[PDB]
Length: 79
Length: 84
Ligand code: NI
Ligand code: NI
Image (cartoon, rainbow over the protein chains, first blue to last red):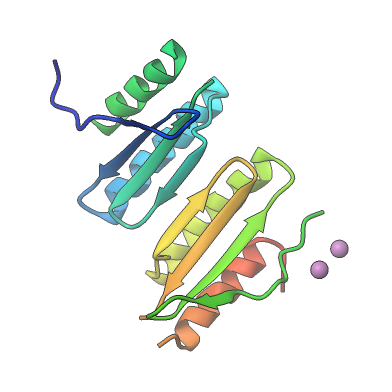
């Protein structure tokens, strides 16, 4: 049990989707920088990232244990 | 090479400008994304949405309009992609 907003599983070949919210552009930008660093280190890239000034939508495609662990590393970065 | 000189597309009910940029590698896409963040901070102008993968970036600009401030932002984004 935790207090993070859940990742939603959807689509025929399943995907994990989550919308992260931030209080300002600077907080969104700082998170996107840490998310880029995470993908660069791991070689694991979400299938899609899209963002505005106060939100980041992330979609992870089925490679599973590894997808859930990457979603947990992203949740840890958000807070 | 990919082509970055195509026109921005005008689309949607309150008009928006839309363009997709494609790159040959993650390094090139990432350099463009980092330069786009610097541009937004320089201008204080932020796209409505930036939507990307490892080899492409889709940008949507909203009406402040649409006027010349939005078109000038679009042209500076083209110059970051190598088109001027
Ligand atoms: Ni052409
Ligand atoms: Ni050519």
